[PDB]
Amino acid sequence: EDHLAKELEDLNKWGLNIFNVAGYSHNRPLTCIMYAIFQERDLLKTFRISSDTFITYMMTLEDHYHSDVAYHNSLHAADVAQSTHVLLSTPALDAVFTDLEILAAIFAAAIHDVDHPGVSNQFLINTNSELALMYNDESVLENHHLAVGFKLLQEEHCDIFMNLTKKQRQTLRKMVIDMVLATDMSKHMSLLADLKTMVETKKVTSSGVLLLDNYTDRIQVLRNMVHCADLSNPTKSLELYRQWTDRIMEEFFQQGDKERERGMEISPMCDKHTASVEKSQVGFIDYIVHPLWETWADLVQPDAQDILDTLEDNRNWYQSMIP
Ligand SMILES: CCOC(=O)c1c(C)nn(-c2cccc([N+](=O)[O-])c2)c1C
Ligand SMILES: [Mg+2]
Ligand SMILES: [Zn+2]
Image 1 (cartoon, rainbow, N blue to C red):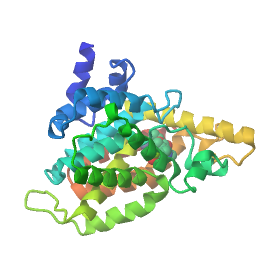
Image 2: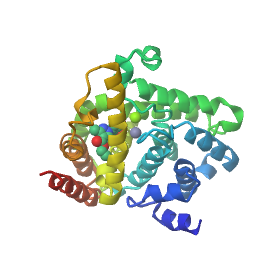
Image 3: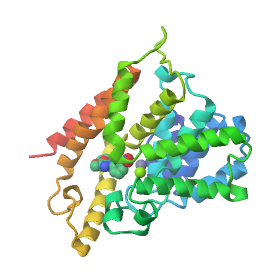
Image 4: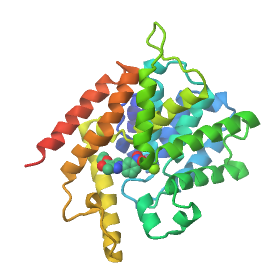
């Protein structure tokens, strides 16, 4: 109600508590936060999208995330979308992207885990699930999330890119596909090397504004920018990071419980009788989150310093939660 408005004063800030907005939106953060972002960047105006259209798409999209799934529900889509919108406002990337590119980034972030079943690519491959067979075991869920996001834009009343050029809509679909595929954890390490080499060639202007040559350079930053938004939980306030931990931990144990019935080998971080939730978070920050965010901060320094502090802080709170 009036509390929703209060929370959207932080739409442009990293400090947005998305759990709160979900509460003041009839349990619909992704719609809310998507509407709120597009209005804020005038994307509805710049791209001839009717609110009527945009709302019905987002609602249908949002209803396609499983609400009975602990982490990969509509709330997480809403959060990557909002994070990506903050990251896109980072000073070291000012006016570096076209609005077409900006529009592709956020939309990507929003459909990026759509219709996620609560289990891993590995589980679906090992169980011979229909999705694995449909997708020949390569970036399975990521391919799917994309398939669904775009299948909904085919229904006339739902196509939000309907008033986009044919050239532009194609450039979009190509950028969006590229980005969602980049959120596959198995491509993480190679994608980290790509960001590292790019940082060693970091060219800018006098104003601490990076210079990107063509597509290759601009879609790589956007690739990694979404990837970091997806792995942004350990850089948020402590109060929101633990809520996110409990949510992913609960999805992972429930995956463990399905792996046990089946008598498949359980994946240690998915084992609810052996796994330290605390150790799981420390390693995730040491081997995955920090190396990424260190390189991102290097790319945009000093824009991400505040974020790196909080990362190394939360990290040590979790270290302390161990005997
Ligand atoms: C908040 C703690 O996060 C986790 O420990 C954790 C681990 C491990 N993997 N992931 C994870 C799982 C599926 C997909 C992604 N990612 O693609 O965003 C990340 C998370 C959120
Ligand atoms: Mg995903
Ligand atoms: Zn995700």
